[PDB]
Image (tube, rainbow, N blue to C red; front, side):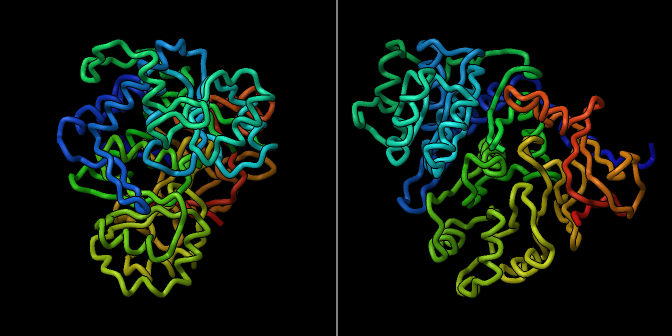
Length: 427
């Protein structure tokens, strides 16, 4: 009883409504302030405002509604990180259509398996990803429609977003009149992520709880205007999807790169006055080697995070030293937990620790051959319970039961311990 660690109350009370309603409300606010940048392409230098994004998200939402999609349908987004990636994501969330972010680097065999699990009716893909999508469509009849993301005109006989929108939208559609669908957030499929890989069913409730964390001044980022983040995390990764979505609710500027480059990354950090940089685990190792860092003005940079990805103590300290920072904004989480359920609290950084338990969550350490709850400073298997835990693996209840027990505890498999202050450490 005294050995179960619980997250504190959330700074703000949990917001009502679905993930789509919650996202629509925020984006609508930032839409009405002209020039508020949602996304920036570091390669192309193109900026897209929240007003452009809100309009496109609302238009795609209604278009998919009139096309015939509802709660029983899914869509796939298969692209490299781009300005248009989140347009179908936001649009589908508004109407309760489950989104399946699909790895654009997948081979034909892996792509089939992923799409086979999520069974999408419409696939939104980039020009680069089209050839593989056409191949898999021949094997999967469920895919009835392919829409091109990064094209203004029609591409290879396939409709662009704009042309697809025109085919279904009423003559005088007003995005500020648009109202997102209301449904049971506890059960409704929001996203289907890939963890032979499995499909992870994440509910609207799952994302609603993440939306609480990301706007939390302790466990996320405080909503301060003119705040920009640079992310090189693939948007189909859990750590890339649920950080970026959260940044949209905060009204932040999200600077992106479809490909990593050392100089472009560091110049983007400097010129866009980035306050938060997000790396994948192996890019942390890269920047421990990088020496160019000193040549750039990174005085605006406040933190470096992964989004909950595993990071070794020594590598974390070396990166922090390069960027002249006290430490890394660490986190622990799995795809099956939506996002990070153990996060470094703002300013409360501790060497080695991956943070404290997030609001609404509980964490315990157990014996590996008993399941007995262990105490402070004692090493064992890390188990978590909270409303961000997935609904289950898609069409695989046996793998779900092996991971999540009847009390709602998820068994991560990782060895951990917590100290007397509540900080967790991955061994």
